Length: 99
Length: 99
Ligand SMILES: CC(C)CN(C[C@@H](O)[C@H](Cc1ccccc1)NC(=O)O[C@H]1CO[C@H]2OCC[C@H]21)S(=O)(=O)c1ccc(N)cc1
Image 1: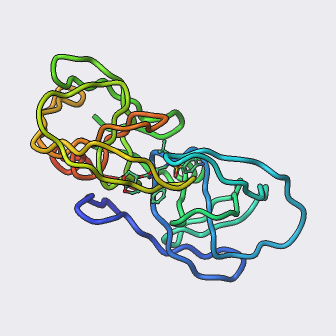
Image 2: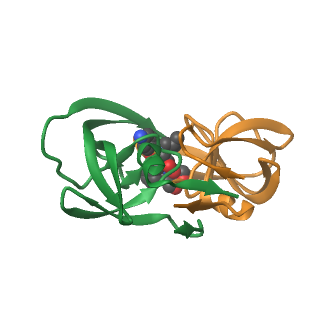
């Protein structure tokens, strides 16, 4: 898939048997989701964006399937206004910017 | 060029005779810069991200040169922690996501 940017680059993601939509976000270091429940241990972290910071649960080694391609890595869970797929996962699905 | 995402997608931008580095950011609807000072009229706006909202000055029809390609459009100026090139400019330089 090559995709243009006239609209938000939203993709369907499958995580822990749940289906969510998330933004492919080259400006995000890490993947952050709001509306999900991951089982198991986690560590507290704070991440910062434009309006300041949020507290997140950091879950490690989480399987995600993004537009039908698999990746494992860190997923942050917290009060983000929009689910975002960050570079830590984008690299695993072979995602690049082109111009 | 094509750009992989192992590192932040930082590019050099020339705006109003000033040189800045900015993140090519597919998760951002609009361009937001901190360390600059554009002349002329503007309108107040608030934009929200992770952490909440910031107050910005909205400047219209601003020329930016991003990695040596020109674009004209809206630039927001405000207390963003990182300069970001958003989709409204990314489309003008023919930027796409590929995987
Ligand atoms: C500002 C960047 C350096 C980092 N942000 C990623 C960025 O893409 C966010 C991602 C984003 C997207 C929507 C809502 C919140 C955050 N976009 C954003 O703040 O865009 C704002 C400017 O244009 C407006 O249009 C979209 C939101 C506004 S971030 O959300 O704060 C962020 C920070 C750290 C991680 N791990 C993940 C995300």
